[PDB]
Image 1 (cartoon, rainbow over the protein chains, first blue to last red):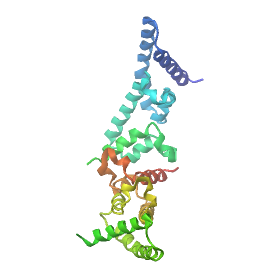
Image 2 (image 1 turned 180 degrees about the horizontal axis):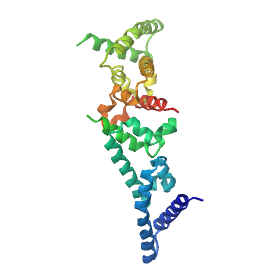
Image 3 (image 1 turned 90 degrees about the vertical axis):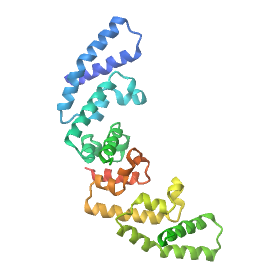
Image 4 (image 1 turned 30 degrees about the vertical axis):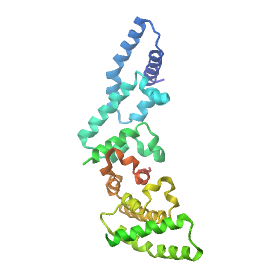
Amino acid sequence: LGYNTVQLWRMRRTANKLMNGKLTTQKEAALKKWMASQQDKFLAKWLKSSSVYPDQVYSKLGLTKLGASAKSSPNYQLYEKYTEALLQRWTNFKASPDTVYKSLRLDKLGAKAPQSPSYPMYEKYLQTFFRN
Amino acid sequence: LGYNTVQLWRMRRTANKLMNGKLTTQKEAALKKWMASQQDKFLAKWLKSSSVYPDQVYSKLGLTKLGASAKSSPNYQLYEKYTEALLQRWTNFKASPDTVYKSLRLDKLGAKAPQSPSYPMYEKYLQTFFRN
């Protein structure tokens, strides 16, 4: 059992407890206090890894499962702050959309690439790259 | 006004007569013979031109307004032979998907590019380019 697997399991678990609500005032704060202390550390770990990418982080944070209610999870803003950092990096590189497509591992999905939760991010980068 | 415009207008009008079912046997044969005689010539002209691209041909052949039933027009298969030739050209050159994107002029459509009748062709070339 790995540290990252357990921690992520705990962040998915904590997110459900916050989405259900009806928590004691001190209990909800103690959960939100523990979540806030995991933001910087997970965001920095994901940015330094060569194997971590958005579709994987989406899955490990519980957002894939949530489907259309993914934005209701406390972990959405964390995933958001991660993709924001990636787009900032790729823009500083002036990466081409074809390079971004491989960063997002969309090449491995074949014909299912358009169904990826990363796909709207890829399309926006591609359009912005080419908007004269 | 111009010869090219008039010929394309006859291709659209001849296509409508076939689809509309009012022709005798002999008039049907004669319209289909005339249409066949235009096939190689239009194909060569569009492939030789640097300013002709699929979305444009699709419109000048009357397909855009047909939507999904565009395949019912006799001109659909002329359009398809044109995009087959393009796809085989770009595949032989090993042109990158980013290059294919601006060959299709999808860059001019910005956030509306995904609604382009050429978009599935782009997505297919892109997926096929990065397979393994």
